[PDB]
Length: 93
Length: 94
Image (cartoon, rainbow over all chains, first blue to last red):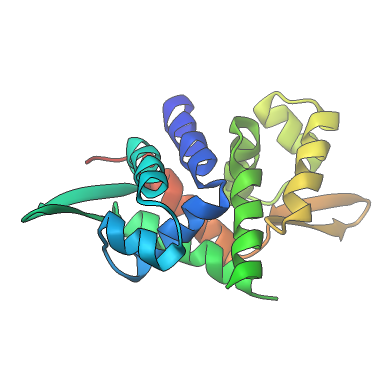
Protein backbone atom coordinates (compact mmCIF):
# COMPACT_ATOMS: atom_id res chain seq x y z
CA UNK A 1 0.00 0.00 0.00
CA UNK A 2 0.95 3.62 -0.95
CA UNK A 3 3.04 4.67 2.05
CA UNK A 4 4.55 1.33 2.91
CA UNK A 5 5.58 1.22 -0.74
CA UNK A 6 7.22 4.70 -0.63
CA UNK A 7 9.23 3.72 2.42
CA UNK A 8 10.42 0.53 0.70
CA UNK A 9 11.30 2.55 -2.38
CA UNK A 10 13.37 4.85 -0.08
CA UNK A 11 15.00 1.78 1.55
CA UNK A 12 16.07 0.35 -1.73
CA UNK A 13 17.28 3.83 -3.12
CA UNK A 14 19.57 4.04 -0.03
CA UNK A 15 20.92 0.60 -0.65
CA UNK A 16 21.70 1.34 -4.29
CA UNK A 17 25.37 2.22 -3.68
CA UNK A 18 28.59 0.27 -3.53
CA UNK A 19 29.96 1.91 -0.39
CA UNK A 20 26.66 1.84 1.53
CA UNK A 21 26.44 -1.89 0.77
CA UNK A 22 29.98 -2.40 2.06
CA UNK A 23 28.96 -0.59 5.31
CA UNK A 24 25.77 -2.66 5.62
CA UNK A 25 27.62 -5.89 5.07
CA UNK A 26 30.19 -4.90 7.73
CA UNK A 27 27.49 -4.07 10.22
CA UNK A 28 25.88 -7.50 9.45
CA UNK A 29 29.11 -9.03 10.74
CA UNK A 30 29.10 -6.98 13.96
CA UNK A 31 27.92 -3.68 15.41
CA UNK A 32 30.64 -1.04 15.02
CA UNK A 33 31.91 2.49 15.70
CA UNK A 34 32.66 4.96 12.87
CA UNK A 35 36.39 4.51 13.43
CA UNK A 36 36.22 0.77 13.01
CA UNK A 37 33.97 1.09 9.93
CA UNK A 38 36.46 3.65 8.38
CA UNK A 39 39.50 1.43 9.14
CA UNK A 40 38.04 -1.77 7.68
CA UNK A 41 36.61 -0.28 4.46
CA UNK A 42 39.29 2.34 3.82
CA UNK A 43 36.72 5.13 3.89
CA UNK A 44 37.07 8.44 5.66
CA UNK A 45 35.27 8.90 8.98
CA UNK A 46 33.55 11.97 7.47
CA UNK A 47 32.26 9.78 4.50
CA UNK A 48 31.19 6.93 6.88
CA UNK A 49 29.26 9.28 9.08
CA UNK A 50 27.57 10.87 6.02
CA UNK A 51 26.46 7.41 4.75
CA UNK A 52 25.31 6.29 8.22
CA UNK A 53 23.10 9.38 8.60
CA UNK A 54 21.51 8.55 5.25
CA UNK A 55 21.07 4.80 6.23
CA UNK A 56 19.66 5.87 9.58
CA UNK A 57 17.13 8.32 8.05
CA UNK A 58 15.42 5.36 6.22
CA UNK A 59 15.73 3.17 9.32
CA UNK A 60 18.26 0.65 7.99
CA UNK A 61 20.82 1.29 10.80
CA UNK A 62 20.50 2.50 14.39
CA UNK A 63 22.94 4.07 16.86
CA UNK A 64 23.32 3.39 20.59
CA UNK A 65 25.66 5.09 23.07
CA UNK A 66 28.21 2.91 24.83
CA UNK A 67 30.15 5.27 27.07
CA UNK A 68 32.01 7.75 24.83
CA UNK A 69 31.19 6.72 21.18
CA UNK A 70 28.21 5.70 19.15
CA UNK A 71 27.80 2.08 18.08
CA UNK A 72 26.00 1.43 14.78
CA UNK A 73 24.03 -1.65 13.96
CA UNK A 74 21.60 -2.88 11.39
CA UNK A 75 18.20 -1.78 12.60
CA UNK A 76 16.63 -5.22 13.07
CA UNK A 77 16.47 -8.82 11.86
CA UNK A 78 14.34 -7.86 8.84
CA UNK A 79 17.10 -5.56 7.52
CA UNK A 80 19.70 -8.21 8.32
CA UNK A 81 17.64 -10.91 6.64
CA UNK A 82 16.94 -8.79 3.54
CA UNK A 83 20.64 -8.04 3.23
CA UNK A 84 21.93 -11.53 3.75
CA UNK A 85 19.48 -13.09 1.38
CA UNK A 86 20.35 -10.49 -1.37
CA UNK A 87 24.09 -11.20 -0.94
CA UNK A 88 23.53 -14.92 -1.05
CA UNK A 89 21.51 -14.48 -4.27
CA UNK A 90 24.29 -12.33 -5.72
CA UNK A 91 26.87 -14.92 -4.79
CA UNK A 92 25.21 -17.84 -6.58
CA UNK A 93 23.86 -19.82 -9.60
CA UNK B 1 34.14 -9.98 -2.19
CA UNK B 2 34.21 -7.33 -5.01
CA UNK B 3 32.10 -8.91 -7.76
CA UNK B 4 29.50 -10.22 -5.36
CA UNK B 5 29.16 -6.67 -4.00
CA UNK B 6 28.81 -5.19 -7.55
CA UNK B 7 26.04 -7.63 -8.37
CA UNK B 8 24.20 -6.71 -5.15
CA UNK B 9 24.76 -3.04 -5.84
CA UNK B 10 23.10 -3.68 -9.24
CA UNK B 11 20.24 -5.53 -7.50
CA UNK B 12 19.53 -2.70 -5.19
CA UNK B 13 19.78 0.04 -7.95
CA UNK B 14 17.15 -1.95 -9.90
CA UNK B 15 14.87 -2.05 -6.88
CA UNK B 16 15.17 1.64 -6.20
CA UNK B 17 11.97 2.57 -8.01
CA UNK B 18 8.33 2.85 -7.00
CA UNK B 19 6.90 1.12 -10.06
CA UNK B 20 9.51 -1.68 -10.12
CA UNK B 21 8.67 -2.37 -6.43
CA UNK B 22 4.97 -2.50 -7.28
CA UNK B 23 5.82 -5.08 -9.96
CA UNK B 24 8.02 -7.17 -7.60
CA UNK B 25 5.40 -7.14 -4.91
CA UNK B 26 2.71 -8.33 -7.33
CA UNK B 27 4.96 -11.14 -8.54
CA UNK B 28 5.46 -12.10 -4.84
CA UNK B 29 1.71 -12.63 -4.63
CA UNK B 30 1.66 -14.79 -7.80
CA UNK B 31 3.51 -15.39 -11.11
CA UNK B 32 1.90 -13.37 -13.90
CA UNK B 33 1.77 -12.41 -17.55
CA UNK B 34 2.53 -8.88 -18.76
CA UNK B 35 -1.17 -8.23 -19.39
CA UNK B 36 -2.07 -9.17 -15.84
CA UNK B 37 0.72 -7.05 -14.38
CA UNK B 38 -0.44 -4.08 -16.59
CA UNK B 39 -4.09 -4.40 -15.53
CA UNK B 40 -3.47 -4.70 -11.86
CA UNK B 41 -0.96 -1.82 -11.56
CA UNK B 42 -2.44 0.45 -14.25
CA UNK B 43 0.83 0.54 -16.17
CA UNK B 44 1.16 0.09 -19.88
CA UNK B 45 2.29 -3.26 -21.22
CA UNK B 46 5.15 -1.51 -23.00
CA UNK B 47 6.29 -0.01 -19.59
CA UNK B 48 5.81 -3.34 -17.71
CA UNK B 49 7.89 -5.16 -20.29
CA UNK B 50 10.64 -2.54 -20.10
CA UNK B 51 10.83 -2.87 -16.32
CA UNK B 52 10.75 -6.67 -16.43
CA UNK B 53 13.70 -6.74 -18.87
CA UNK B 54 15.67 -4.54 -16.48
CA UNK B 55 14.64 -6.73 -13.44
CA UNK B 56 15.53 -9.86 -15.42
CA UNK B 57 18.99 -8.51 -16.49
CA UNK B 58 19.99 -8.43 -12.72
CA UNK B 59 18.26 -11.76 -12.08
CA UNK B 60 15.46 -10.55 -9.84
CA UNK B 61 12.75 -11.99 -12.11
CA UNK B 62 12.63 -14.86 -14.54
CA UNK B 63 10.25 -15.80 -17.43
CA UNK B 64 8.98 -19.27 -18.43
CA UNK B 65 6.84 -20.20 -21.43
CA UNK B 66 3.35 -21.53 -20.53
CA UNK B 67 1.48 -22.41 -23.75
CA UNK B 68 1.58 -19.22 -25.90
CA UNK B 69 2.51 -16.44 -23.30
CA UNK B 70 5.44 -15.74 -21.06
CA UNK B 71 4.99 -15.94 -17.32
CA UNK B 72 7.11 -13.88 -14.95
CA UNK B 73 8.06 -14.76 -11.41
CA UNK B 74 10.47 -13.68 -8.75
CA UNK B 75 13.75 -15.43 -9.52
CA UNK B 76 13.97 -17.55 -6.36
CA UNK B 77 13.22 -17.68 -2.64
CA UNK B 78 16.08 -15.45 -1.70
CA UNK B 79 14.60 -12.62 -3.85
CA UNK B 80 11.17 -13.32 -2.38
CA UNK B 81 12.58 -13.37 1.11
CA UNK B 82 14.58 -10.11 0.63
CA UNK B 83 11.49 -8.39 -0.65
CA UNK B 84 9.03 -9.64 1.92
CA UNK B 85 11.31 -8.78 4.81
CA UNK B 86 11.96 -5.25 3.40
CA UNK B 87 8.15 -4.70 3.01
CA UNK B 88 7.52 -5.89 6.52
CA UNK B 89 10.19 -3.52 7.90
CA UNK B 90 8.67 -0.59 6.05
CA UNK B 91 5.26 -1.60 7.32
CA UNK B 92 6.33 -1.64 10.94
CA UNK B 93 7.18 -0.05 14.40
CA UNK B 94 10.39 1.42 15.94
